[PDB]
C-alpha cells in the first residue's frame, strides 16, 4: 500500500591567503672626515 | 739616515744642553735655530722620519718655543711687543711644522706602530697645552684668530689620532682646547669659524661616543653648547643632532641616566628663548630618528608648554605649536592618562590659539605653515578615532548597513580641513620667495603625508597638486632624493589616471634629479629601479613592449629588489602589477623566447601576479599597523605603529595601494567569469572601506559588487547594492537619478572627480544590465547610450583638469585611457542587443562603431574586440553555412565562411592567453562549427578547449600556491601540470599550427584503453542554449572523430530535454513538502516515469545513430577491413569527407545497429545515393554481426555547463559500461602524470577496505539512515568515524588525506564542515562517497560555468568522487548505499567500483528518480 512520506536529504539550513610575515628593515650602518 | 738622524738629534741635544748651560741670551742661537727650522722645512717636502728622531725633534722644538717665550718675556721683546708677536708667529710656524710632521708620521704609521704613535700623542697633548698657554694673554681679533689657527692645527693632528683609534689620546689633546672653549665667556672668540670649533668638539664627542663614555661626552656637549654661546642655534643644530644620537646609544643599551639629563635640566639658567629653541631642535632631531621616541618627545613638549607664557601673544603662538606636537605624540600613544587631555582636544585648542594669533608681517609664513599642520593633524587624529571605533564596532558585531551610512556631515567637515591645509601650503610655497619657516623639512614630511591621505580618500588630483608642491620644496631644499621620489610619484599617479605624456616628462625629471645622488646609497638603487619600472610601464603603454620587457627582466633580475625594507617591498608590488600588465597582452606582442623568460620568473596568469601583489600589500599592512584593520579578531595583535615620519606616509600609501589592487583583482576576475573570488575580494575591500569610513571607495566597490551579482543573476541583491550606491552618490553631491542631465563641463564633486564619474557611469551600466535582464528594453538601451555619451565627456574634463593642474601649454596627445573599458563594455552590450533586433539599423551601426573604437586601441581592449568580432560573425551568419564543412547532415575575405573563420581566429589569438570563460567557449565552438572536417585536429582541439575554463584558471592559481608553499618549505609534477594547463605553452606560428602540435602531444599522452567523449552545445546567440550538439571522440593511436547533431529541426530538441529536467526538479521540490502520503507517492511515481521518458529521449532523439561514438572500439580486425572497403565504396555515393576511423568505431557495434540507425547514417552520410549506401552498410553489418566481441576499456564524459545535469550514464547503451566524468581532458592527462610520479596511491595500488572514515547523521535530522547504517558501519573492521554529532574539521582533513575511503551519509556534500577551500588546501587520497543531495551537482548561475565541491575534490586529486546529481530522499538512497557497499565490499579484492555502482542503481524503488541520481567523477578504482 501507501507508506509514509520520506524526508528529503537536503541540508535545509574563496579564501584570500592569510598575510605572510615580511622581514624587518635591515639597520643600515650609520663617516668622520679628515681636518 | 738613522745614524745621520741620530747625529742630527745629538747635535740638537748638544745645542739644547749648551743652551741650558747658556746664561747669556741665546739670541744668536735663536737665529741659528731659525736656520735649522728652515732646513727642516726644505726636508718637510719629503716628510720622512723615525720615532726617536721625531721625539728628538719635539725636544729641540720645545727648547725653541722656550727661547721664543724667554725672548718675548725678556724686556727686549717685552718692550718690543711686535718682536714678541713675531716670536709668537715663529713659535706658530714651528707648531705648523709639528702638525705637518705628526700628520705624515700618522699616515705612514702601521697598525703595529700605534705604540710609538701613542708616545707621539703624549707629546702632541703637551704641544697643545703649550699652544693654549701661549694663547693666554692674546688680545685683538688677529690674536684670537691666531689662537684659532693653533686650535685648527691641533684639530688636524686630533683627527689623525682619532683615525688611529687613539680616541682617548685624541680626546685628551682636544680636552684642553675644548675645556677652554667650553669655559670661555660669551663673545670672547666671536671671529673663530664655528665649523673649526665643531670639528674639535666633533672628534672628542664622537670619541666619547664610541668609547662608550656617552655620559662624559654628553657633558662636553654642554660645553659644546656653552662654547657657541653667541653663535646662532643653526651652528648649534649640530650639537643637537649629536646629542640625540648620544642619547639613542643609551636607549639602545638601556641606560637611563642619560635620558634623565635633558636640556632644561642640563643648562639650568640659559635665557628662555634660546633654551626653548634648543628644546625645539632636540624634538626635531628625535622626530627624525627611528625607534619609539614617544616619551622623550612627550617630555620635550611638556617643558616647551611649561615655558610658553599663555598671557603673552607670542607665548600663545608657542603653546599652539607645542600643542600641535603634543597632539602628534598623543595621537599614536597612550599618554592621555598623564596629560588628562585627548589628542583631539589638544589640536582643537591649538587651532583656536592659532586663529587668535595675528602675524607680524614677517612671521606670516610660519603662521600659514602652523595652521596647515594643525588642520592636517586634526584630520589625522579624527581619522584614527574613526578607525578605532570601526574596529571596536566590528569586534562587537563579530555588514550592508554601515556601507550606506558612511557619508555624514563629518566627511564634508573632515575633508574641508584637508583642502584648507592644502590651500594654506600652496599659498605659502607658490610664491617666488623662499618660505621663512623654521624647518622646511617638516613642510616636506607633512606634504608627503597629505598626498598619501589624498590618494587614500580617492582624490588623486589634489594629491598631484600636493606632490607638485613637494617637488617645489625639494628643489628649494636642494635635496635631490626627495625630488626624484616626488617625480616618480607624480609619474606613477599620472600613469594611473591615463596620461602617458606627462608621465614621460616627469620620469625625465626624476632621472635628471637622480643623476645628482651618490650612486652607492640605497636610495639611489631604489630610485633607479623605480625609474626603470616606470620606463617599462611607459613602453608598455606606447607599444614598445620588446624594449619594455627587457627593462622589466633587468629590474626583476636585479638582486637589490629583494632587500629587507618596506620601500623595497612596496616596489616589488608595482613590479608584480607590471608583470600582470605584460602578461595580459596577446602573444603577437612579444617573441616566444621573451614570453618564456617572463613566465619563468614565477608568475604565469595576470591574476596570479595581482594576487601576489595583494598578499604582499597585506603583509606590509601586518608589518606596519598590525592586523586589526584587516581582521576583526578579538585582540588579534598589538604591534606599535612606530611613527617616524616615513612610517606615517607608508601607512596611508599601503592602504591606498591595497584598495587599488583589490579593484584590479575584482575587475580582472569578474571579467574572466570567476565571480566567487571576485566577490570575496570585493567584500574584503568593502569591510576595509567600512572601517576607514570612506564613502567614495565604498561606492566604487559596491558598484563592482552589483556588477558581480548581475553576472550571477541575483537582481534583488544587485538592486540593493545599486540603491546603496545611489544613496552614497546623492549624499556626496549634497555634502532617473539627478546626477545625470549635467552639462558636458561641470564642477560638482561628481564631475570634478574622475573616480566618482567612473562610479556613476558603472552604476548606469549595471542598471542597464538589470533592465535588460528584467525584460525592460528601451530603458537599458537608453542607459547604455547615456554611458556612450558620457565617457568621452568625462575624458575631456579629465584632460582639461590635468592641463590646469600641471600648467602645460601643449594639451596631451591623447585623452586619458581610463574609461575605455566602460565604453567598450557598453558597446559590447549594445551590439549584443542588436543581435536580437536585426530590424533596427542603429545597433548595426553601433557594431561597426565599437569595432573601430576597439581596433584603434590595440592591444589594450582585446576581450571587447573579440566579443565584437564574434557578434559580427553571428550577424554575417544570418541548412546552414556549416553544412558544407561536415560529412553528415540530418536525413572581401573570399566566401562568408572563410571571412568568419578569419575573424574568429583573430578573436581567438586575441583572448587565448587569458580567456574569459564564456567568450572562449563561444569562439571555440563557433570556429569548430565553421571548420568541421576540413581541419579535424583543429575542430577537436577547439571542442576540447571550450569546457571547464574557470576550472583551468583555478587549477593554475592552486598550482602556484602549491609551488610557492613548496618553495617556502624548500615540484616536477607540478611544473608539468602547469605546462599542461598553461595558455602560453604554444610555439610561434599562424592558427592553428601552434595549437595543433600542442593538441597532438596531448593526444599522444592519452592512456591506453580510454575513450574521451566531449559533449558540448554550440550556441548561436550568447546567453541562450543551442540545439546543436558537438561530439568529439578521442582515443590513443586513433585520429579524433568529431560530429555535429542539429536537434532543433525535429521535435524533442536538447533545449526541450533541459526544460523537462528542470520542470521535474521543480515539481519534485514542490512535492517534497506534501503532508499527505497518498498524493506524495503518486507524484513521485509520475516524476519517475517522466524521468524515464527523458532518459529514453536522450538515448533515442538527442543522440540518434551517433550513440556508438561512446562505445569501446572492437579489437578484432573486422571493422578495420570493412571500413577500408567502405571508404572507397562510399566516396562514390556522395560522402564528402571519408573517415575510416569513424566507420571503424560505428561498425564495432554492428550487433546493436538498428536498421533505423543504418538508414539515418546512410541517408545523411551519402545523400546523393542513399539507397546504395544503405545497401553496403547493411551488408557490412551482416558480415560483422556476431563476429565483433565486446572489449574491455573505460569511457570518460566531458560535458559542458548545461549537459552535466542530465543523467547520461543511465541511458540504455551506457547502463552496462564503466563511465566516469571529468572536467576536461587535461584532467585525465594530469591524473596520468600524477600516477607516473606516484602521488596517487589509490589509483596505483588500490583501495584498502581497512581504512575508511564515515560521517553518519551529523545534525540528527535523519533517524532511518542512522538506524540503518550505524551497526553495519561500526561492525566493519578498521573503520572509524562519527555518528550523531558534527565532525571537527581537523578530523575530516585527516579522513580525506590519510584514508583510502571516505563514506558520507548525510545532508548535502558535507560543505558545512568541509568547505571547498578546506579540501582544496589538502591532497585527496580517498575515494569520496558522498551520498547526500546534489553532492555531485554543478550549480549554473546565469551564463557562468557550473560550480560545486566536486571540482574542488578533483583538483585536490580525488581518484573517484561518487555523488548525487539531484536532490534525493532518505530511504531509497539508504537502499542504494546499502546495495552498493554490500556488493563492492563483499566482492573481494580487485573489484571495480563502477560496475557495482551501476548494479546498485537497480536497488532503489523509484529506479530512475533515485538510482539515476548518482554519478562518478574521476577514474575507475578497485580494491587491492
Ligand atoms: Zn556635474
Image (spheres, coloured by chain):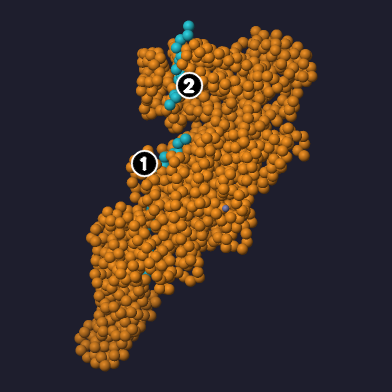
Q: Quarter-wise, where is residue B312 in the image?
A: bottom left
Label annotation for residue B1333:
2
Instruction: Give the structural element (helix, strand or loop) at label 1.
Output: helix
Say if residue B1243 shows up in the picture: no
Q: Nearer the viewer, residue B733 or B1147?
A: B733
How far from the left and from the top, in percent, is residue B837?
Answer: 69, 35
How far from the left and from the top, in percent, is residue B1363?
Answer: 49, 21
Rounded to the nearest angstrom, the CA distance separating label 2 from label 1 is 36 Å
Query: What colour has chain B?
Result: orange
Q: Label 1 marks which chain's residue?
A: B
Instruction: Give the structural element (helix, strand or loop) at label 2.
Output: loop
In which quadrant of the rendered image does the N terminus of chain B lie? bottom left
Residue at 72% from the left image edge and 33% from the top image edge: B877
Q: Nearer the viewer, residue B442 or B596?
A: B442
Q: Is circle 2 on the same chain as circle 1?
A: yes
Position of A11 relative to B195 (above/below): above
Position of B1117 relative to B1039 (above/below): above
Residue at 51% from the left image edge and 21% from the top image edge: B1069
Q: Nearer the viewer, residue B286 or B1018?
A: B1018
Q: Label 2 marks which chain's residue?
A: B
Q: The cyan chain is which one?
A: A
Whether residues under marks 2 and 1 lie with C-beta atoms below 8 angstroms apart, the answer is no
Q: Name the residue under label 1.
A: B395
Say if residue B1185 shows up in the picture: yes
How far from the left and from the top, in percent, is residue B1419?
Answer: 52, 22
Amino acid at each position: 500500500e501507501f507508506e509514509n512520506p520520506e524526508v528529503p536529504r537536503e541540508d535545509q539550513q574563496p579564501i584570500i591567503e592569510e598575510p605572510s610575515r615580511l622581514q624587518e628593515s635591515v639597520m643600515e650602518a650609520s663617516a668622520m672626515p679628515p681636518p | 739616515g738613522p745614524q745621520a738622524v741620530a747625529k742630527l738629534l745629538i747635535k740638537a741635544s748638544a745645542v739644547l744642553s749648551k743652551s741650558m748651560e747658556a746664561p747669556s741670551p741665546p739670541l744668536r742661537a735663536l737665529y741659528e735655530s731659525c736656520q735649522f727650522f728652515l732646513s727642516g722645512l726644505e726636508r718637510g717636502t719629503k716628510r720622512r722620519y723615525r720615532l726617536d728622531a721625531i721625539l728628538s725633534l719635539f725636544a729641540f722644538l720645545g727648547g725653541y718655543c722656550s727661547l721664543l717665550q724667554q725672548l718675548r718675556d725678556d724686556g727686549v721683546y717685552g718692550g718690543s711687543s711686535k718682536q714678541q708677536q713675531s716670536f709668537l708667529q715663529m713659535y706658530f710656524q714651528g707648531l705648523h711644522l709639528y702638525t705637518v710632521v705628526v700628520y705624515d708620521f700618522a699616515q705612514g704609521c702601521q697598525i703595529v706602530d700605534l705604540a710609538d704613535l701613542t708616545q707621539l700623542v703624549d707629546s702632541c697633548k703637551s704641544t697643545v697645552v703649550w699652544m693654549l698657554e701661549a694663547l693666554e694673554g692674546l688680545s685683538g681679533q688677529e690674536l684670537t684668530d691666531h689662537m684659532g689657527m693653533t686650535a685648527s692645527y691641533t684639530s688636524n693632528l686630533a683627527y689623525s689620532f682619532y683615525s688611529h683609534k687613539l680616541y682617548a689620546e685624541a680626546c685628551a689633546i682636544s680636552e684642553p682646547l675644548c675645556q677652554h672653549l667650553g669655559l670661555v665667556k660669551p663673545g670672547t672668540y666671536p671671529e673663530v669659524p664655528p665649523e673649526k670649533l665643531h670639528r674639535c668638539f666633533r672628534l672628542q664627542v664622537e670619541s666619547l661616543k664610541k668609547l662608550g663614555k656617552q655620559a662624559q661626552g654628553c657633558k662636553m656637549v654642554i660645553l659644546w653648547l656653552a662654547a657657541l654661546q653667541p653663535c646662532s642655534p643653526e651652528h648649534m643644530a649640530e650639537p643637537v643632532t649629536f646629542w640625540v644620537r648620544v642619547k639613542m646609544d643609551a636607549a639602545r643599551a638601556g641606560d637611563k641616566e642619560l635620558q634623565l639629563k635633558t636640556l632644561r635640566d642640563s643648562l639650568s639658567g640659559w635665557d628662555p628663548e634660546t633654551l626653548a629653541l634648543l628644546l625645539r631642535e632636540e624634538l626635531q632631531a628625535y622626530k627624525a630618528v627611528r625607534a619609539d621616541t614617544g616619551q622623550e618627545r612627550f617630555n620635550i613638549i611638556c617643558d616647551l608648554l611649561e615655558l610658553s607664557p599663555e598671557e603673552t601673544p607670542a607665548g600663545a603662538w608657542a603653546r599652539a605649536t607645542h600643542l600641535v606636537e603634543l597632539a602628534q605624540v598623543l595621537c599614536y600613544h597612550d599618554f592621555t592618562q598623564q596629560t588628562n587631555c585627548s589628542a583631539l582636544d589638544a589640536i582643537r585648542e591649538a587651532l583656536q590659539l592659532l586663529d587668535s594669533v595675528r602675524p607680524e608681517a614677517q612671521a606670516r609664513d610660519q603662521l600659514l605653515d602652523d595652521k596647515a599642520q594643525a588642520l592636517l593633524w586634526l584630520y589625522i587624529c579624527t581619522l584614527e578615532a574613526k578607525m578605532q571605533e570601526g574596529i571596536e564596532r566590528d569586534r562587537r558585531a563579530q555588514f550592508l548597513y554601515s556601507n550606506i551610512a558612511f557619508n555624514l556631515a563629518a566627511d564634508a567637515a573632515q575633508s574641508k580641513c584637508l583642502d584648507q591645509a592644502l590651500a594654506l601650503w600652496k599659498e605659502l610655497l607658490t610664491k617666488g620667495q623662499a618660505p621663512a619657516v623654521r624647518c622646511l623639512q617638516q613642510t616636506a614630511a607633512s606634504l608627503q603625508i597629505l598626498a598619501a591621505l589624498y590618494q587614500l580618500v580617492a582624490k588623486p588630483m589634489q594629491a598631484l597638486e600636493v606632490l607638485l608642491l613637494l617637488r617645489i620644496v625639494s628643489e628649494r631644499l636642494k635635496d635631490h632624493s626627495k625630488a626624484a621620489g616626488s617625480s616618480c610619484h607624480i609619474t606613477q599617479l599620472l600613469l594611473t589616471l591615463g596620461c602617458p605624456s606627462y608621465a614621460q616628462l616627469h620620469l625625465e625629471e626624476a632621472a635628471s634629479s637622480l643623476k645628482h645622488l651618490d650612486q652607492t646609497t640605497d636610495t639611489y638603487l631604489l630610485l633607479s629601479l623605480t625609474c626603470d619600472l616606470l620606463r617599462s610601464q611607459l613602453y608598455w603603454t606606447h607599444q614598445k613592449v620588446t624594449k619594455g620587457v627587457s627593462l622589466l627582466l633587468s629590474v626583476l633580475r636585479d638582486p637589490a629588489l629583494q632587500k629587507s625594507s618596506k620601500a623595497w617591498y612596496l616596489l616589488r608590488v608595482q613590479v608584480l602589477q607590471l608583470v600582470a600588465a605584460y602578461l595580459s597582452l596577446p602573444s603577437n606582442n612579444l617573441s616566444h623566447s621573451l614570453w618564456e623568460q617572463l613566465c619563468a620568473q614565477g608568475w604565469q596568469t595576470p591574476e596570479i601576479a595581482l594576487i601576489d601583489s595583494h598578499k604582499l600589500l597585506r603583509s606590509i599592512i601586518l608589518l606596519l599597523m598590525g592586523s586589526d584593520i584587516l581582521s576583526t579578531q578579538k585582540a588579534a595583535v598589538e604591534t606599535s605603529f612606530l611613527d617616524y615620519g616615513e612610517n606615517l606616509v607608508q601607512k596611508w600609501q599601503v592602504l591606498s595601494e591595497v584598495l587599488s589592487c583589490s579593484e584590479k583583482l575584482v575587475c580582472h576576475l569578474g571579467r574572466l567569469g570567476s565571480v566567487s573570488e571576485a566577490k570575496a575580494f570585493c567584500l574584503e575591500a568593502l569591510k576595509l572601506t567600512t572601517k576607514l569610513q570612506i564613502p567614495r571607495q565604498c561606492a566604487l566597490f559596491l558598484v563592482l559588487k552589483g556588477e558581480l551579482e548581475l553576472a550571477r543573476n541575483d537582481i534583488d541583491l544587485c538592486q540593493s547594492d545599486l540603491q546603496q550606491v545611489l544613496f552614497l552618490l546623492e549624499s556626496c553631491t549634497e555634502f532617473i537619478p539627478n546626477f545625470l542631465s549635467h552639462s558636458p563641463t561641470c564642477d560638482c564633486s561628481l564631475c570634478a572627480s574622475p573616480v566618482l564619474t567612473a562610479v556613476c557611469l558603472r552604476w548606469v551600466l549595471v542598471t542597464a544590465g538589470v533592465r535588460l535582464a528584467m525584460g525592460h528594453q528601451a530603458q537599458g538601451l537608453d542607459l547604455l547610450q547615456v554611458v556612450l555619451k558620457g565617457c568621452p565627456e568625462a575624458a575631456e574634463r579629465l584632460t582639461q583638469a590635468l592641463q590646469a593642474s600641471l600648467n602645460h601649454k601643449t594639451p596631451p596627445s591623447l585623452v586619458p585611457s581610463l574609461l575605455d573599458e566602460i565604453l567598450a563594455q557598453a558597446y559590447t552590450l549594445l551590439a549584443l542587443e542588436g543581435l536580437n533586433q536585426p530590424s533596427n539599423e542603429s545597433l548595426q551601426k553601433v557594431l561597426q562603431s565599437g569595432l573601430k573604437f576597439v581596433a584603434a586601441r590595440i592591444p589594450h581592449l582585446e576581450p571587447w574586440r573579440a566579443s565584437l568580432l564574434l557578434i559580427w560573425a553571428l550577424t554575417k551568419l544570418g541548412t546552414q553555412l556549416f553544412a558544407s564543412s561536415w560529412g553528415w547532415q540530418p536525413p572581401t575575405g573570399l566566401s562568408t565562411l572563410d571571412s568568419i573563420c578569419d575573424s574568429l581566429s583573430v578573436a581567438f589569438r586575441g583572448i587565448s592567453h587569458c580567456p574569459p570563460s564564456g567568450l572562449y567557449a563561444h569562439l571555440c565552438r563557433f570556429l569548430a562549427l565553421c571548420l568541421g572536417h576540413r581541419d579535424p585536429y583543429a575542430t577537436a582541439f577547439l571542442v576540447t578547449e571550450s569546457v571547464s575554463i574557470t576550472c583551468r584558471h583555478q587549477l593554475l592559481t592552486h598550482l602556484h600556491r602549491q609551488l610557492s608553499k613548496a618553495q617556502k618549505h624548500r615540484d616536477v609534477p607540478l611544473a608539468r601540470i602547469q605546462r599542461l594547463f598553461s595558455f602560453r605553452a604554444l610555439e610561434s606560428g599562424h592558427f592553428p599550427q601552434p595549437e595543433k602540435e600542442s593538441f597532438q602531444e596531448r593526444l599522444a599522452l592519452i592512456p591506453s584503453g580510454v575513450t574521451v567523449c566531449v559533449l558540448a552545445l554550440a550556441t548561436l546567440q550568447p546567453g541562450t542554449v543551442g540545439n546543436t550538439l558537438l561530439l568529439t571522440r578521442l582515443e590513443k593511436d586513433s585520429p579524433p572523430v568529431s560530429v555535429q547533431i542539429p536537434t532543433g529541426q525535429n521535435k524533442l530538441h536538447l533545449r526541450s530535454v533541459l526544460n523537462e529536467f528542470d520542470a521535474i526538479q521543480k515539481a519534485q521540490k514542490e512535492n517534497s513538502s506534501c503532508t499527505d502520503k497518498r498524493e506524495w507517492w503518486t507524484g513521485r511515481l509520475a516524476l519517475d516515469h517522466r524521468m524515464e521518458v527523458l532518459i529514453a529521449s536522450l538515448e533515442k532523439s538527442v543522440l540518434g545513430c551517433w550513440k556508438g561514438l561512446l562505445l569501446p572500439s572492437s579489437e578484432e580486425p573486422g571493422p578495420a577491413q570493412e571500413a577500408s572497403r567502405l571508404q572507397e565504396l562510399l566516396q562514390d555515393c556522395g560522402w564528402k569527407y571519408p573517415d575510416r576511423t569513424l566507420l571503424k568505431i560505428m561498425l564495432s557495434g554492428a550487433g546493436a545497429l538498428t536498421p533505423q540507425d543504418i538508414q539515418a547514417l546512410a541517408y545523411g552520410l551519402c545523400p546523393t545515393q542513399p539507397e546504395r549506401a544503405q545497401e553496403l552498410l547493411n551488408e557490412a553489418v551482416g558480415r560483422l554481426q556476431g563476429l565483433t566481441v565486446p572489449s574491455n576499456s573505460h569511457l570518460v564524459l566531458v560535458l559542458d555547463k548545461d549537459l552535466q545535469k542530465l543523467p547520461w550514464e543511465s541511458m540504455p547503451s551506457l547502463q552496462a559500461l564503466p563511465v566516469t566524468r571529468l572536467p576536461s581532458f587535461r584532467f585525465l592527462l594530469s591524473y596520468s602524470i600524477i600516477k607516473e610520479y606516484g602521488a596517487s596511491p589509490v589509483l596505483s595500488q588500490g583501495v584498502d577496505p581497512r581504512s575508511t572514515f564515515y560521517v553518519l547523521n551529523p545534525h540528527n535530522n535523519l533517524s532511518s539512515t542512522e538506524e540503518q547504517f550505524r551497526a553495519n558501519f561500526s561492525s566493519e573492521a578498521g573503520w572509524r568515524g562519527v555518528v550523531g554529532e558534527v565532525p571537527r574539521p581537523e578530523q575530516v582533513q585527516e579522513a580525506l588525506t590519510k584514508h583510502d575511503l571516505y563514506i558520507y551519509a548525510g545532508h548535502g556534500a558535507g560543505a558545512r564542515f568541509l568547505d571547498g577551500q578546506a579540501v582544496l588546501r589538502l591532497s585527496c587520497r580517498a575515494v569520496a562517497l558522498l551520498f547526500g543531495s546534489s553532492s555531485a551537482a554543478l550549480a549554473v548561475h546565469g551564463n557562468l560555468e557550473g560550480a560545486g565541491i566536486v571540482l574542488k575534490y578533483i583538483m585536490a586529486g580525488c581518484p573517484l568522487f561518487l555523488g548525487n546529481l539531484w536532490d534525493v530522499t532518505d530511504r531509497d538512497i539508504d537502499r542504494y548505499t546499502e546495495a552498493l557497499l554490500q556488493g563492492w565490499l563483499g566482492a573481494g579484492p580487485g573489484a571495480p567500483l563502477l560496475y557495482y555502482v551501476n548494479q546498485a542503481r537497480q536497488a532503489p524503488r523509484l529506479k530512475y528518480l533515485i538510482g539515476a541520481a548518482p554519478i562518478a567523477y574521476g577514474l575507475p578504482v578497485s580494491l587491492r
